[PDB]
Length: 314
Ligand SMILES: CC1=C(/C=C/C(C)=C/C=C/C(C)=C/C=C/C=C(C)/C=C/C=C(C)/C=C/C2=C(C)C(=O)CCC2(C)C)C(C)(C)CCC1=O
Ligand SMILES: [Cl-]
Image: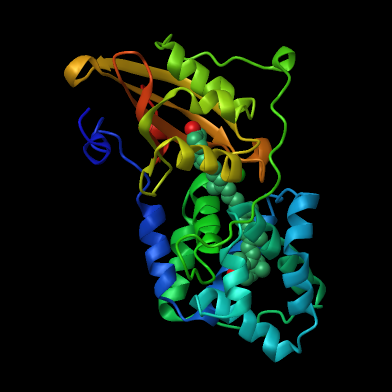
């Protein structure tokens, strides 16, 4: 209850799926052309059983100029551009890409994937064989749960491009209006009646970010899977609006314990669906909340769990 960074240690029994950042770190080592081929291979294979939702209209408009620029290039330059992104080279295209929210980056690649499939953008060379390191990276990915697989792909997409500057322009999709109060569902969590936790889940499921942020302490933080804590209301609200639209949180069960100085720690496990996959992928998630004496959120971590055996009382 003293520092955000120390709160990261609550519920240390929770086995997170650290194969995901392990696998990203291996992937990130690879030659850029192998990075692109590996993801193309993983995307095609995944596409046999799992269809990516179409990118939204707003997102596509925001990426349109950059997409058109690539499509207008000669094939060799197309491949160079894609390699630039994967290598995190400093180019205008890479800087533009880095200004984008994850969803806009994902929609940019969705479009390129389609164009590569159709042959209008330079495809991976015919009969391309992955490097030794890359083949093993792909094998690891394909052995993971689908929730882990899609998190690897997202993290690979988000990592591309080049950031120059701390206060650079941030482009995101427009913010959706909150769900009308009448049509809102309420979660039920075995063992957990805590109104802060329940309001957290319900407000996020309604896209009600302005209500959600009011649950947090001024200095409070939210820690997304495999990322550092996002600290303070401005940054946490920004993150909700840019990256947390249209989720479906399906918490199942939890456990509630005292913490130092009148705090309460609560762990919840359940599933989450992203709008990119809907009900076809349920990620196994834990939430770990540290609530202050008045019930506001000082810290919440969201963990992708190593396996379903990590869900409480499987
Ligand atoms: C790149 C590339 C390609 C294309 C690749 C493509 C098109 C790839 C597309 C990949 C896609 C669309 C991946 C989407 C992943 C989304 C996830 C993991 C969302 C998780 C959300 C969670 C857990 C949120 C949970 C949360 C909860 C519960 C909270 O309580 C608080 C909020 C928080 C957010 C933390 C080609 C195929 C063209 C080949 C070349 C190439 O390189
Ligand atoms: Cl998402």
